[PDB]
Structures are given as structure tokens and as C-alpha cells.
Image: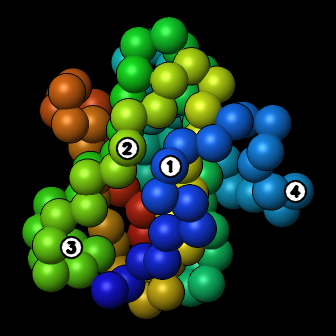
Amino acid sequence: DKATIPSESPFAAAEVADGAIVVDIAKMKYETPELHVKVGDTVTWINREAMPHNVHFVAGVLGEAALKGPMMKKEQAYSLTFTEAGTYDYHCTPHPFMRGKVVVE
């Protein structure tokens, strides 16, 4: 797999790590749709709105299986540590018009 998951469950926005690379989700959009990060970095998405959202990577992108992350309620967060360079597209499972990518370099 090309990503590690620190927490399987969503956690509170207050519990996000100090040096965290945060992508906010608000107004039915990932606020930074193209994020450039380097190998070994942890990206944390935080849902800032009441409608639940997640990140979903289809099969073969971060691993053999799809990684359909947990639904994040308002002010919940979810992290992924990227371990291999490449371009990783993702969408929100209930709202597939929400699309973004992480470019790990």
C-alpha cells in the first residue's frame, strides 16, 4: 500500500497533530483540490460543515483494494500518511462531483 492510516475512525479537529497538513472541506468542496506533499507526509482532511463527507480512492490507486474512508461529521478529521511518490485522485463517496488529488513528490 502507498498510504498508512493513523486512525481508522474519524477524530476531533482539536486532536489534529501540530505539524499537520490540513485540507478543509467546506461548501461542498475540498478547499485545496490539488495538494502537493512529499513522501512520508501525513495529510489531514477536516470537515468544516454539517453535511458528512469522506475521501475515497478507488482500487489500485493507494493499494489493491479501494480505500473508502469513514464519514466525517462536522469538525471531525481523518489522516493518511503517503509513503510513495505519485498522483492520487480521490472523490467523496456520497457526493462524487467533489474531486481532488494529492501529488506526492
Res 97 → quadrant? top left
- Which mark is in front, 4 or 2? 2
State if disc 3 and disc 4 touch (CB < 8 Å). Answer: no
Q: Is residue 73 above or below residue 70?
A: above
Residue 62: x, y in percent?
28, 75
Q: Which mark is residue 70?
A: 2
Image check: 39 left or right of 86?
A: right
State if disc 2 and disc 1 touch (CB < 8 Å). Answer: yes
The number of numbered badges drawn on the structure is: 4
> In the image, what residue type sits under mark 2?
Pro
Residue 27: x, y in percent?
46, 13
- Gap between marks 1 and 2 measured at Cα: 7 Å
- Which mark is in front, 2 or 3? 2
Q: Residues within 10 Å of mark 3 (few under 14, many from 20)?
A: some
Residue 14: x, y in percent?
81, 36
Q: Residues within 10 Å of mark 1 (few under 14, many from 20)?
A: some
> In the image, what residue type sits under mark 4?
Asp
